Structure formats: C-alpha cells, structure tokens
Amino acid sequence: KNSLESSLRQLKCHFTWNLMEGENSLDDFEDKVFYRTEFQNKATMCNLLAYLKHLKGQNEAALECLRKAEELIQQEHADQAEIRSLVTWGNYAWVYYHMGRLSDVQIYVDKVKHVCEKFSSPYRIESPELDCEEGWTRLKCGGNQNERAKVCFEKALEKKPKNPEFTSGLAIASYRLDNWPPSQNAIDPLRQAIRLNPDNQYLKVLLALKLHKMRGEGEKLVEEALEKAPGVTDVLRSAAKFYRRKDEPDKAIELLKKALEYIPNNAYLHCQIGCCYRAKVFQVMNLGKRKLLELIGHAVAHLKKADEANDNLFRVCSILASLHALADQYEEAEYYFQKEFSKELTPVAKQLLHLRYGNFQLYQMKCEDKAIHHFIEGVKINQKSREKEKMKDKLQKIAKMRLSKNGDSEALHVLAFLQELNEKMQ
Amino acid sequence: SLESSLRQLKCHFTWNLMEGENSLDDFEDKVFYRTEFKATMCNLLAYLKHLKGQNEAALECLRKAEELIQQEHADQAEIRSLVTWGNYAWVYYHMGRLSDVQIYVDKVKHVCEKFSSPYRIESPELDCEEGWTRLKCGGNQNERAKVCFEKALEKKPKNPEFTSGLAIASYRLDNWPPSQNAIDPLRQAIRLNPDNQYLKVLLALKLHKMRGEGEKLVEEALEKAPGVTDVLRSAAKFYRRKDEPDKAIELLKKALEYIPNNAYLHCQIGCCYRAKVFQVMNLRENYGKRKLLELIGHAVAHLKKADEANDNLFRVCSILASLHALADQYEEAEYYFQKEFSKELTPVAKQLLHLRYGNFQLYQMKCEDKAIHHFIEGVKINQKSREKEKMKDKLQKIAKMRLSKDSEALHVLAFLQELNEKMQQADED
C-alpha cells in the first residue's frame, strides 16, 4: 500500500544512517575512508566501501562488496549469521533499488523481515516518541546528560523531520551543548576497556597518550603494546605520535617507516612522518647543512605525497613553504606560499600566513616592501592574536626608523593607525 | 534472570542517568530546583524517590503520571505509557513485588508485539556495528558513535567490544571537541513553535554572544510570557551579559515571587547585585559608601541562601568572602575564607585564593606576616598564571623593604631570581 522506498527507509543499514552529514565533498570523503581502511580495524569494511561505490555511481561494484561481506560474516561470526547480516542485506535492498531492480530488492526485504520477526523483542520497540520522551528526561537531568539528549532528538527527527517538539528538543540541547561543552572523562573507559581487552594493544597506547596529555605509566604502556603487536599499524601510527610528543623524533620516524612498509601509499602516514622529520629539523637546530639538507629533503618528499593525495585533507603548503625556505630554496618556497593564499582560511590562520610570508620577504628576499603589505593586511584582520601583536611591533619598528630618516609621510599614517589600536586597549 | 530481562525495557532504570554523579543529594537538588520552573516530570521524580529507598513513594508519581498521560494522549495512551510501565515494573522488582512486576511486563509485551516494525530491530549488536562505522567516518560522527556504544552497553553492559568502542569514541571526542551549530535549530524551532517564548530568549543569548534583534527577541518573549520562569531567568542573563544588570535584577525578583526559595534563582540574583557592586565602584564621582553597602548587603543575603541550600552546586564562598571584605565586616570575611580553603579546589583557584587572601591580610587586616605566607604558598604551587606573577611581585616589594631595614628576605630574592631564571628561557623559545 506504500512506496517501496518508505519501507526501505525503515531498514537499519548505511543508507539510513546519515553518514554524509556536513561532508561538503564526496571525493574528500572517499579518500578519508580509503586511507583509514588501510588500518585493519572485519566486514563493516566491505559495507562502508560498498556505500561509497554506490555514491560514486558504481552500483555494480557495490554488490561486489556486499557479497564479500556476507562471506566474512558467514565464516567467522558463522554460528550466528542471521542478525549479523541485517545491515548487509538492507544495503543490498538499497543498492538494487537504485539500479531499478525491484526483484532482488524484494528478495532482501524478505531475508530482513524474516530475521526481524524471529529475534524481535517483546520488551522494546522503536520510536520517535520513545527517543523524545527520553531526550526530555536527559535534558532535565542536564550536565553530561545533554549530549546523549541531542542524539535522542536527532534520532526522532530523522524519522519525522520538521516536527515541533523534537525540534525544540534539538535546539535547547544544542544551545546547552555549545554554551557548556561536555567533559570527556575518557581516561576511565579506556581503563575499563583495557581491563576487558588486554590483548588489544591499541587501547593501551590511547591510555598512554591521554595520560601524557593530563600530566611512568605511559612509557610502559607503549612498550608493552609495541612489544605484543609491533606490526599492527594503528599501534605503530599512534605510538609514533606518543614519541613525537615526548620530543623523540627518531623513535617516531622509526615506527612510521615500519608502518609504511605495510601500506606505503597511506597519505596520513606520509603526512605524519613528514611532520616528524620537520620536528627533528627544529630539534637539531635547537641543539649542520648536510643533515638539515638531507633531513629537510625527507620531510619535503613525504609532505609532497600528502599534498598530492588530497589538498583539502592535507593542508600542508605553509609547512612545505617554511621548509623549502630553510633549505634556501626560495623558488619552491614562493610556489607553496602562493598556493596557501588561494585556499580557504580562518582569519586566524590567514594572519599567521601574512606573518610567515612577510618574514619570508623581510629576511629571505630583499623586499621589505612586500613584507609591509602583509603585516598591514595581516593587522587589518580583526582577530585577537599574538601574531597580530607581533606584526604590529614590526610595523611600528619600520615606520619609526622611517621618520628617523625623514619626519616618512607614509609612516606617519601607519604610526597613527597603530597608536589608534593601543589607546583603545585597555 | 528476571532482571536480565528488565534490562530490555526502556525506562529510567535502563537510561543509566546517574552516570558521572557521585552525590545523590546534589543530583536530587539540581533536578528539584529545575522542577520549580508533565508526564516526563512525574517519571523522573518517581525515579528519584526510588533512588532514595522511598519506593511506595515512587509508585505514587507513577500512578499520577499515568493518569496524566491518558488525558494528554488518550488515543495514544498505550504507546506513551511504555516508559511509565517499565518503571512500575522495576520499582516493584526492587520492592520484591514480583507478582505486580509480571503485570507491567505483560502489558509491555502486548503493546510491543502490536507495534513492532517488521523491518528493524533494537539490538546491542546493531548499535555496535553502527558505532564502528560512524567511528570510521570520524569527525562529527564521533559523538554519534559514542552514543551507539553507550546504547549497546545499557542494553548489554560489561561487554569487552562495546567498551572498546566506547573507550575510543571517548578518547577522540576529548581530543577533537565536536562543532556545535545551535543558531539554525533555534530559528527552525522558534518558527515551528511560535508560542514558546523560551526559545526566543535562547536565540537572543546566542546572537549577542556572536556580536540589534537580540533585544527584539527578548522583549517579545517577555511581553508574551511575563510569568514563565524559564523566560524571566534567561532574559535576566541576557541583560547582565548586555551589562544592564538592573533589569536583570528586576526580572529575577519577579521569578522569585513564583518560587520564593529557589537556590538557582537566589544564586543568580545574588551574582547580579554583585555585578552592580563592581560597576558602582568604577565611576567614583558621587555613588557613595552608604549605597555600596546597601547593595553588598543584598548580594550577600542572596548568595548566602544558595550556600546554605548547597555547598557544592553553589561554590560561592570565595565571592561571599570578598564581599564582606569590601564591606569592612571582616569577621564574616574570615569565615568564608576559612571555609573556602577546606574544600576541593583547583591549583589555579587555590592561587587566586592565596592571593585574594594575601591581599586581604595586607591591606584591611594589617598582618604583613600572614600575607607573606600565602604569596609564598601560592607561588610554591606548581601552576603558571597572571596571579602567580602579581604574587611574586608583592613579595618583591616587601622583600626589598626588609633588605633596606631582615636578611631572611634575601632568600625571597634568591628564589625569586632563581624562579624567573628558568622562565625567560621559555619566552625566547
């Protein structure tokens, strides 16, 4: 008595979760997932890949994944496949429907309906009104209970968008969530989790990293985790992070080299390691031309691969630029500086860029004039930053040393301008 | 197990609402003071009374809630009534009234069979899978992925995997705090709810916080609903933020009429009088002292009702202290200072305090010795802040004086120079 769609809308699977919310870009999202899947966290994999291929218009190839998934489901979670396939089947249902295939869609809505009548609880249904009655309860509890409350109102609106009550709920919840951001007492469930799964070494590295964030336990946690599963890339990846943060670049570079052997095209890996080489450069400078030249070479090769993979996910041009700068490569430096200006930029960052480039003009190039354009355009940007305040100090310096020579006319404007900002603040 | 199956019913007993609360009193208060401001209400309450052994007391609200639901939703009584029944059943189980328990479960099973969807099922393994997926998309799906594993634990608590999920979701939400759009949902909800003035005030507070229409919204809601406390209370916050506290105070006074003794109201109005007490001081060209004191008198009385009601929700001793201090009624200032020290406090707060007190001890009280102790202790604390400096600084002045007239102070210079030693090496970095 109803559109085959309306019925498909009620199935639980990837199509009915809402995974593209706020994803401006399907290529971005495709790369973001393909790069993350190279870390072997299972069959949920094949479903996520299917969902994408469908979105890429490759429906044919999507079935290819759904199929490999229900093979994994049958072999490993084998004794009980009926409930484990619920989403895989509903993904089939949706893929076929987009292929205009009414016949198999119907098959799978059947394999679903069956397993659903067989394991249905006589205790709990599904409801917008249930999710809502709960969201109000949590809201009236308040505190960390309001984040769970937002989801509640979200879940009630997916089914029935535009409702007045559920929308009240969402709005109040959200306002509270923006005003008083929730506390993540993660350190606990990480502990509970490690208790439950000692074998899983990834969990240990997260305890180890969050401890160091809230500062002996950590170092041992990572060493156990590195000891048991050196190969597992989630472990190497996040271990390396651990050491970069403890100012141990060699340990991190070593780790990430190892992970790269497993998946040598991973962009997150090239980015990470490039950054670690960059961390060694500064450290070395703090504590030699061939080494800087060779090291700077490394960071550059790696960051280039990330920038080439996906310019939006790997915003790495500033760094490549300041890096080509150290190596006295001034042409490359330019190329990458001019590339950062074309892209989107938080006023905050656009400032840091004007400063960075300004200094590059001021010290590397002979052009103080160019430097001035940026400190100025950088300071006109209304963001309270140490960077604005650093570019001020510099423009006062240059305007003064100018009136030193000729009491010149242009400076008398910059000088006043600046003095107009100091008087206000206070 | 009877309980194993009572986990399968959606009711406050399975919402795990006490997660992160280590005091039941603080909880019952937060809730009770917000209930001075509904079927949802009676159930929440029923849950409270139960939580305090008063189970016949809980059954009461439940009967009332049910009665109320039949009026609001007579046609939907059986579907609205789900949550209530699941409470009934749990309450009875905790009273050992097994036979009445079977009755409310028997009602729930019938309703569920009647209304079950043939396409979807609620399952902890279907929440877990979704959680893993959202986890793998990352980003904003992270908070949504936490709930998924949580939802899986309430249904199936103690599982290795579901907790693994929850661990990781939670690590990442800490690392990368989700973005929070609230401006859209509010306009969308105001349009959909033209009679709920509260939303309008909320939107106004979010606008002004992004700086007009701010005042437009508030004034409409005020004239549409001059008796709704949610509205009066949030409008007052608006006007304080606006800096025009005087209107704030007037609103709060109005809300107080409806609820004489609300600790939240009192704390809020109290803080307002205090904001005026500052403002008055800045002009300083005549008001006078006889006026400060009329105002200090007002704030102190309202903050005191909150302190009395709660010493944990209303952490208002540091404020009371420096309020009697300005007053010159030092004896009282002692009390609130003594109480503040003997309480859990942040290292940074315990500096401010060492400071606020150090100053007190120097200027009004004339004990130079005592201040010295605190500036010392507040600088010994391993924290970095503006107050530590203002504090190292007062020990600079007072050290120099001892040099000019003991030699003890020479060591106050040593530690001083010794401290600022390491510090400059950081600024250069």
Image (tube, coloured by chain):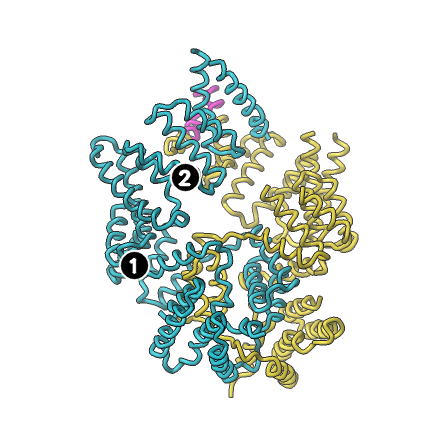
Chain colours: A yellow, B cyan
Between marks 2 and 1, how big is the CA–CA gap?
31 Å
Indicate the position of residue A187 as horizontal and vertical percent values. Answer: 59, 51
The residue range painted magenta reads A400-415
Label 1 CA crowd tier, 10 Å (few <14, some 14–19, many 20+): many
Q: Residue at x 26, y 36 (%)?
A: B280
Residue B229: numbered disc? 1
Q: Across the whole image, how many numbered discs are drawn on residues?
A: 2
Chain letter of the residue beneath label 1 in the structure image? B
Residue A338 is drawn in which quadrant? top right
Task: Please report contact status of discs 2 and 1: CB closer than 8 Å, yes or no.
Answer: no
Q: From what the image shows, is residue A261 above or below residue B39?
A: above
Q: Most prominent secondary structure in the magenta stretch?
A: helix
The disc at residue B421 is none
Q: Residue at x 50, y 69 (%)?
A: A155
Closer-to-camera residue (B334/B289): B334
Q: Mark 2 points at which residue?
A: B340
- Specify the subunit that label 2 lies on: B
Q: What kind of residue is marked 2? A: Glu
Badge 2 marks a residue whose secondary structure is helix
Quadrant in which the C terminus of chain A appears:
top left
Q: Tell which of B384 and A109 is nearer to you.
A: B384
Residue type at mark 1? Thr
Q: Does the magenta stretch include residue A333?
A: no
Residue B79 position, x and y percent, is: 44, 79
